[PDB]
Image (cartoon, rainbow over all chains, first blue to last red; front, side, top):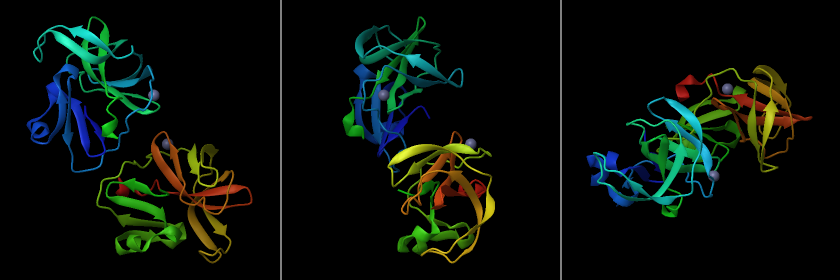
Length: 138
Length: 138
Ligand SMILES: [Zn+2]
Ligand SMILES: [Zn+2]
């Protein structure tokens, strides 16, 4: 539910992908924590064609939507976790905000449509993986 | 595009239905100017489960969305047109607003989802056919 559905695509955190995701793989990138898989049914979401840097996301741990201001996508060194070794993550946008394990998957939106998806968190920051350059999705 | 798509339903003005609409008929009611037909693909709209009486609709002739205040659904005598004889139309909600032939089909929405669809117009009023009682749709 922590997925973007655009066209015949389902976009998820790569660390959260299901076996069925991999069985219907379209595209994946560890350095971004993104995986896209094929769908049978047409999705309801649109990808934002803008450079907005404020928006609203869904926080899973709080079950609320929050307004947020987030930095332009950058290369960020992200510490080791149970999902990845310490590595450079690209396309990562950071906001001051509540963050708990399980928040990954939460969808970030602006008036133009979907901006990104929660991927990282810690130290009082929420990191969203930007999807706006993925023009092939829409 | 002047259609509501909810579940596997397509909801249209009955006077605008296509032959394919009738070939896949689920439900229709002349007294409301509504027709619902079957779809292959899951729709993106939700029906408003509320009694809101202000909202926004799309005006076809102006190609703009407009904010509107509309009366509670009533039985309204509607004059003869090329589509119906003079008759009582039920479930009809009226707002002061721009209206031209071709505006029928425009979708009215509030924060809870889809409220109604433009059905009538004239004398400085826009009449929307309420769909909120159609709970079987969602
Ligand atoms: Zn935007
Ligand atoms: Zn409402």
